[PDB]
Amino acid sequence: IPTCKITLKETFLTSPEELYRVFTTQELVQAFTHAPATLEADRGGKFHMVDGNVSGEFTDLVPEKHIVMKWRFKSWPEGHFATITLTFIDKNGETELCMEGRGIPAPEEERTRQGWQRYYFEGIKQTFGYGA
């Protein structure tokens, strides 16, 4: 499978604590994705979101600092996971979120970029009021 790497940076009007909670709380994920979610906020823990269209496993969780996960869309080749790292940086009580994704199927680059920008970043900002 040819793959690609993407890097996204987004600033939120909330603290790293609050943003990290949004990414790692099943009921908050349910709210911003508008769908039932299951999320085990543990190293080794599984997640399943948007009618099972997104799934994966957390491989490193450092509260308020970083999340590393194996992550896929349901349509990707079976057993194919991207590795996504989210880093939470405090900038004056606001949060700079750096997302780095590796191992994204190359045909899926724009779907995955737009999915992250619209369904994570815009979704979180609009649900919780974390700025434009």
Image: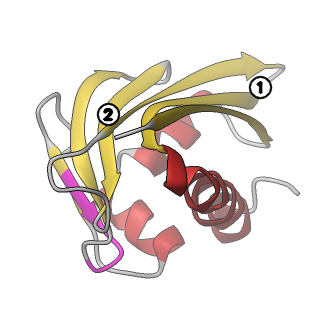
The C terminus: image quadrant: bottom right
**Rounded to the nearest whole Å, what is the CA distance between mark 1 and mark 2?**
25 Å
Residue at 75% x, 62% y is: 129
Camera-near label (1 vs 2) is 2
Q: Amino acid at mark 2?
A: Met
Q: Which residues are magenta?
A: 47-51
Residue at 28% x, 69% y is: 37
User: Which residue is the site of mark 1?
Assistant: 93
Residue 19 lies, with reference to residue 67, above or below; the image says below
The percent position of residue 44, horizontal first and vertical second, equals 11, 32
- Mark toward the start of the polypeptide (1 vs 2): 2
Q: Is residue 17 rendered to the left or right of residue 23?
A: right
Report crowding for label 2: few under 14, some 14 to 19, many 20 or more residues within 10 A (C-alpha): many
The percent position of residue 2, horizontal first and vertical second, equals 43, 38
User: Which residue is the site of mark 2?
Assistant: 69
Residue lying at the far right in this picture: please name it.
132
Q: Secondary structure at mark 2?
A: strand
Q: Amino acid at mark 1?
A: Gly
